[PDB]
Length: 50
Length: 45
Image (cartoon, rainbow over all chains, first blue to last red; front, side, top):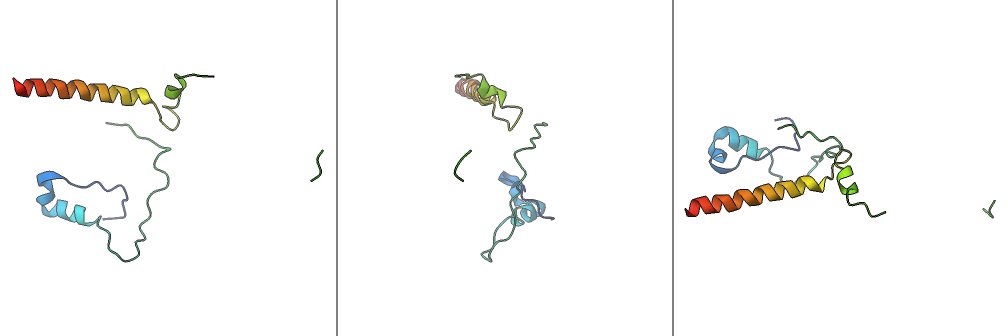
């Protein structure tokens, strides 16, 4: 629940669980002058670990 | 105040520093293409 600008959505049937619902809801933007900061250092350090 | 070379391979040399290897993209496209054609053929069969 901490601010994670790279939060990935849950798609498909997994979107219909309470945990996935909370994860998906933690991303919607209210029209209240948004102040969440997109990360600035996200391209100069690449992690291709699979 | 008065005074007094065309190297396409270079496109792959940037894959380590600010990764820009287009060969990775070409490989991904080719793999996805063979995957899609084979999948279509198998589903049709």
